Amino acid sequence: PPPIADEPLTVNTGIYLIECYSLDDKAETFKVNAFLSLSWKDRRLAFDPVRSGVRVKTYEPEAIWIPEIRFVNVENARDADVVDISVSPDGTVQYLERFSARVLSPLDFRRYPFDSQTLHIYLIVRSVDTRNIVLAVDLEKVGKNDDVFLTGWDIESFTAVVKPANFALEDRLESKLDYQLRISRQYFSYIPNIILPMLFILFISWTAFWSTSYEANVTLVVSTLIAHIAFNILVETNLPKTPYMTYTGAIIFMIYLFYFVAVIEVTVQHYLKVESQPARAASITRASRIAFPVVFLLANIILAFLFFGF
Amino acid sequence: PPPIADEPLTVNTGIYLIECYSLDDKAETFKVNAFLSLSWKDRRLAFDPVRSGVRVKTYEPEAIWIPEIRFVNVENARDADVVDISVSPDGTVQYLERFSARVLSPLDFRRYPFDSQTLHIYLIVRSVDTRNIVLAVDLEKVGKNDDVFLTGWDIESFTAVVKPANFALEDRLESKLDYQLRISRQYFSYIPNIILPMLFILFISWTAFWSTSYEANVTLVVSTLIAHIAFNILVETNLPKTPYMTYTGAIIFMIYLFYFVAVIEVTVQHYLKVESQPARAASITRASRIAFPVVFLLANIILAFLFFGF
Amino acid sequence: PPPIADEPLTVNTGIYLIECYSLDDKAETFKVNAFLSLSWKDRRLAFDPVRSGVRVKTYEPEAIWIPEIRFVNVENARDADVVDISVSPDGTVQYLERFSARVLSPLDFRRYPFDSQTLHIYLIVRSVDTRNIVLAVDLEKVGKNDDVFLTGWDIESFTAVVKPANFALEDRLESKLDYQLRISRQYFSYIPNIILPMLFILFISWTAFWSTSYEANVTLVVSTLIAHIAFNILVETNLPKTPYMTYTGAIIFMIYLFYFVAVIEVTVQHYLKVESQPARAASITRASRIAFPVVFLLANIILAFLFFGF
Amino acid sequence: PPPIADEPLTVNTGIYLIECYSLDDKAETFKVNAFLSLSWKDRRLAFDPVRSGVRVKTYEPEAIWIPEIRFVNVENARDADVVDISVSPDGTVQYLERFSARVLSPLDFRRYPFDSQTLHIYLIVRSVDTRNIVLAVDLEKVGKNDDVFLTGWDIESFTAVVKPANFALEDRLESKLDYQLRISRQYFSYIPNIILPMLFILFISWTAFWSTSYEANVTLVVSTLIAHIAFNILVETNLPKTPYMTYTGAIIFMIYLFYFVAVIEVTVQHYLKVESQPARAASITRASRIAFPVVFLLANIILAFLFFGF
Amino acid sequence: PPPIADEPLTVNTGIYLIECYSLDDKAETFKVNAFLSLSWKDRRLAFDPVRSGVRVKTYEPEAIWIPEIRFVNVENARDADVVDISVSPDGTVQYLERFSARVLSPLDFRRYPFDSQTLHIYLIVRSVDTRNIVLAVDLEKVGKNDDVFLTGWDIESFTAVVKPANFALEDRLESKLDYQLRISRQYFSYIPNIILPMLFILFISWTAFWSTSYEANVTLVVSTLIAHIAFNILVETNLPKTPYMTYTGAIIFMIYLFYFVAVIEVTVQHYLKVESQPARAASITRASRIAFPVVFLLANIILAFLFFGF
């Protein structure tokens, strides 16, 4: 039984995150638990403050007409429990539920360990005989407890784009709002646990430039090549199959090359030292010790700049 | 209370994907969240436009007769929430729910990293005293937001096969529709992460054709053989037990052979160099360096052609 | 309100699988989604075909007495949605639900990669003042779509044991039916992915019978011993802790022995070649090259026969 | 509306396991699915056998007063479906539900691979104006189908401790019953898969007592030390963080010592053989070959006895 | 229908844990199952003890006004079942539910294997026309069975902060209570399983200070470096991505350095022993054997003190 009116019924929205959690990098989802604030005028139930009852009248949801606000990007329907409906004399309604959804918002892994993200909760509403348009009220959208968790991320700001998006979808017009949760990753645990060890074993790897024993040089270079696949797989595991190239994706693949030519060199510093001309072998081996740790530190700047600097 | 009529009641369908996600290669499933559009004529509730009310009349689902449309290939029942029922004067109904199912459609891993797929949502409807036949209406089936995700895949087109399939199943006739979602995989992340490294360690492996030390030649060939099991298992892990042979399945097994004979050669370039006739050893070792990287590049064409070229 | 009668009320059953899936080897379960067909005579609602209505009368489940059929081997209760109840004039009821359960049926991993299985869905019904006995009607039990999936298995035949099992259980008699789903595994992907590689690395392993360098002989035999634990664990992982011995369980343990004595030999072809009598060392080493690949191929027949041949 | 009476209302209980499953070692839980039998006298509904109806009268649960029996050790509430309520003339009620809970009972991993366990389902009932006391009736508690699964365990006996435990808890008295499920583990698959291989690689490890090449002696002893961490982690993984010491916990740590001194010896059988006095080196190396496999077999008895023998 | 009164309605709370379990370190959650005790005065239902009925009157929840107590830090809504409502003559209510939630409380991994924690359950209540304030009653909050499990932790004490926290949140005042569960970890299983083995392989690692063979010195130092990544990953796995530095996080990274310079030394005790001046090589090698095991034991004190001592 919708509210008879002369024009577009405006419904004022507002979210208040109470709990964030389980941001699943692989899945590209996260779980929220917040307040939802709705508010419209339905003069059909204005009420003679003096003639009866008191200041405001409480209603069971079954009694009044209430606008269906569905979330757009959600897995299964949202999971809500109604907190208070309060009707004011002029015919103004004050709705308040407490929901918990798992929301589906893409991420940009282009700077993976150093990335920043911007999550979206959507909210549309479908119209009938009267057009409905949503809109943000900011005192009910300061939504964010001073206790919002989200392990592994720093939460920067929850806000909404005031102007809504009004498609026509299936011979009826809908109205959509944008709620943005801005977060940056907490990279750090990434250093002592992935970054440094990935370098350490790369340095060791090419300690075999101050060595002459092919045996201890393949035992050296190959054993590290393995420990680095150990890392490649570890990282390529808590990460989805992007169709672009990650930052940690490149410097992990670049490092596959500094193993290939490393193994080239040690193999050539050999079919050149069995060939009776070590004049050259321990001439190449000498350059390696310099061209390697430079071309690395040099390409890492090229790569680093390519991603963040640009 | 079904709609008394002279013939087969036709119910016009239409899906509109709003959200795709969680295509589980192992499981052979995916999760959809879309609009469902139904529409039939039930003259039993034609309504005297002028004598009362307005243009259309809204009903609660409890009030009218509504056709049960069940999905065929789904795990547990579909998970729906009703959006609007609108009855037009002639006795025409306009149904619209918003469901979320996890659908079960097979995939063809024959070209695994370079495969294309075609997912199915099915929709049957069981008849009673009057036969029901379904059918697609295409303005309600343009179903696909310009935001449909599906990580790891490019979505090519959502459509339906207009003619339905009319079995008789259990002393009553049913009618089935085919909705097709065409996708191709985003192979790429497969290259820097699986393909190239699988080659790199294969090349290194047979660097021991320019080497004479059995010790550094088994330390060479065997350590790579291991790093390749590391890859075999990684890949054979995000993939179900097909009864056919994958593409990546072959070139991963072919590569097991280029390790076996590699280890054969180095073992024969030895019980032939301890046997006082290295005339032959460093005669075989010489061919290897050519027959190997050719027979590979050559069989890879044979294999590649066998799968895609045919 | 049960159906007053002179004798055992017979209820005719029939299952029709629509979807099979998620056979969990570890868990020993699988998920089905089928039709359930019930049918009994309840003369209490015979109906004067001519005096009113039509051929058959449809009822809401709340209206009639319906027999509770529970599944015996299920995790939580079954998950059903009712499709049509049709009462015929003589007082005959025609029930039809569509359920989805996850069923719990043991498997026999005695021939693991080459096993055949026989799954069970059970169905009992508890009696009250009148005894209930179930029984199979085969036109409603041809249950199996021509599209039944079950990744990794070939489905051989769905059927039911016509005679039911009538216990007395808790001062009331119950009646149980046996529905059998016969499947054999699709072994294959097991070959290029587990079987062959397990052999390959075993052959390589004992390439060190044509080698004299303890160092390259321990680097040889030990590195493969490792790659085989890689396989042992991979396999012992998608498999439950049977109290019997798997086929792949034996030939994976037998192969642990052909590594132990391999390492024995190479260690004895040494404290016998440092002991100034290689007359014997390269006398033992010679036999190895024959006794090994024979005792293997020979025990594999003994083992293979022991399991399948018997 | 409780049953007015002169004294403690006695409610006769009885469980009948129908399905056991998913005993989660890590979690310390298991999932049951059984019958629950309640039975009390509520004279308030004695009923004149002759004056009306028949032998017994069936009731919907809404109609009579029924005692709330809650399980004590359960995760979320139990999950029940009511099977039959039967009231006898004297005013005796016969309740029967079929529930499925996941129960939380500790285990004793002190003999891990050879342990025996004793699971508990608890059952309390809270009193009001009349005291309630529970108690076991054994014909309704022979609860255990001849088909109870529980993969990996042998089920020894389901029983109940007849005397209940009557606390006063929160200004009201409660009554608690003990149902005991006695199981012992099926150790076996533990042998071919963990125990033997853990020994095999330990023997190999100290094959380097009949060897002189430090290189092949560190390649020998260290490569096995690794394969044993492979096992340590595998086992320490399907097991919770006990604050006591497991059996398999000790003999897995003892074995870490027979690697440490192994590596000590081979390192001392070297800074004593480069030290121009091998008189001693191949004097120590000789003892090792005996003190090792004895001190092992000897401590294993000490340890084995310490755990089981005591 | 709230209780008309002159002032802030006080509602007396009290929790009684019955079951603790599934403290998920990674997730930062735990699962509780306890009693909830509420109690307020609602004179509106005072009752003439003598004129009718008895001492106290039992009510169904539908009948009286009951205050909604929601938990603040919970995933989805709490999961409750009502145990008894008892109204006393003065108009005093006695509520008692039994709930099960999974609670979300942060942890402090700063001393990881030796940490102590303090979990929180929160409880707010929203006011309407009359202000509500909560408060703890301690005879109903002795909440903790003498059987509370929580595998892996010692439970120290369950208590509540008597003074509540009274925000104004969304044009209405709320009142919040603090329930604290104090636990310390059971570190131990951490020693035989992680700590000791991490040291053992570190000692072995630098056994190559009494060795001269680069080959057996890289085979020595590198093979252990690997076994330590085995441990790094094992530990970094049952632990969330803290933005601070764990204790076990440091001494696991410090140990990465005692591998780096270890590998430095052995590589320099070589390009100094091939350069014809071993005067220095076996001069450095000599210091190593002392500076290493001292700088370790020394920094471990610095680190240990830094974390616990401060």
Image (cartoon, coloured by chain):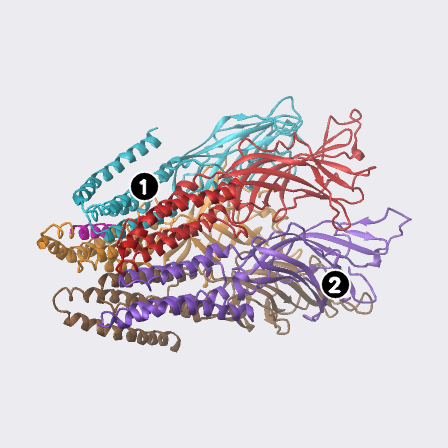
Chain colours: A orange, B cyan, C red, D purple, E brown
Is C309 or E138 nearer to us in this picture?
Answer: C309
Q: Residue at x 59, y 36 (%)?
A: C17
Q: Which residues are magenta?
A: A256-268
- Looking at the rendering, which quadrant does residue C36 occupy? top right
Chain at numbered mark 2: D
Determine crowd level at label 1: few under 14, some 14-19, many 20+ residues with C-alpha closer than 10 A: some
Tell me, yes or no, whether the highlighted magenta stretch contains residue B103.
no
As measured in the structure, the alpha-carbon distance from the residue carrying label 1 to the one carrying label 2 is 70 Å
Q: Is residue D270 above or below residue A245?
A: below
What residue do we see at 55% from left, 47% from top?
A: C28
Residue C61 appears in the figure: no
**Residue A60 at what x, y percent from top left?**
63, 52
Q: In the depicted view, which residue is nearer to us: E90 or C81?
A: C81
Q: Position of residue D192 (x, y in %)?
A: 47, 54
Residue A257 belongs to magenta span: yes
- The chief SS type of the magenta part is helix
Please identify the quadrant where the C terminus of chain C is shown. Answer: top right
Q: Amino acid at mark 1?
A: Leu
Instruction: Report which residue position mark 2 lands on.
Output: D135
Q: Secondary structure at mark 1?
A: helix
